[PDB]
Image (cartoon, rainbow, N blue to C red):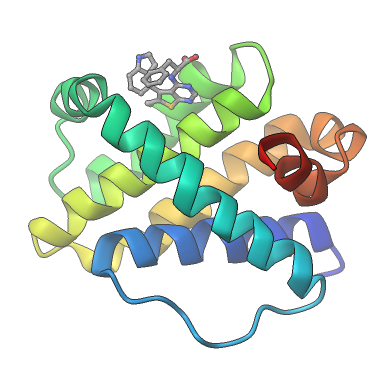
Length: 151
Ligand SMILES: CCc1sc2ncnc(N[C@H](Cc3ccccc3)C(=O)O)c2c1-c1cccc2[nH]ccc12
């Protein structure tokens, strides 16, 4: 507790992954910094859906290489994301791609009756993002900078 960037990041990524997987939109209000979290999630529905639709073939190719089947295969994805995501350049384009790929995997997890793995997947993405890019996210004004960037 007393890490608002982490709390706000978890809220936005977890809601996106669950909405993408199930189709149900959460009507429950956002916590502290509501305006920003709603806009961020609206941005993700536009830009995130756009990445998955536009690059379906590349996403399907990667999903098949990673061969996700169960909780163990999801736990394994964290190491891949550190290597693929964290060890590349940092920009909102790559951040949206990571979260979009999470949504792509979450839809995959729903289709194989592995919904229980969607929350850990969301936790793992948020940890990779916030733990490895903390100072960059702060410099870029966090989720307010994300919304302004993709306006
Ligand atoms: C673990 C899956 C991840 S996390 C991740 N985090 C950031 N960026 C990524 N991709 C962009 C390249 C890119 C752009 C649009 C569509 C598809 C790919 C980048 O690296 O700049 C990926 C990937 C990823 C997913 C699917 C195929 C992939 N090919 C190489 C990475 C990658």
